[PDB]
Amino acid sequence: AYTNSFTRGVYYPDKVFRSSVLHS
Amino acid sequence: YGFQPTNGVGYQPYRVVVLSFELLHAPATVCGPKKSTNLVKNKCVNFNF
Image (tube, rainbow over all chains, first blue to last red; front, side, top):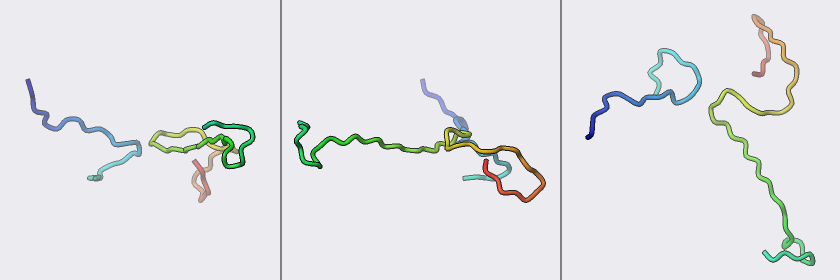
């Protein structure tokens, strides 16, 4: 079988805190 | 290499060590020689963390 993720597999690219900031 | 003791320089064996300092994204690691410590706040200061 195969299935569809929707919005899955997002990890914090590294340390360094951060707040409201649509960071790219 | 067939090394032999009667070889002109530039054909004698040299031993090499390559140190490579890397900085991933951890919290810290090895360094030079520590010194002092303390911790001042509420004052313009010159700091090293």
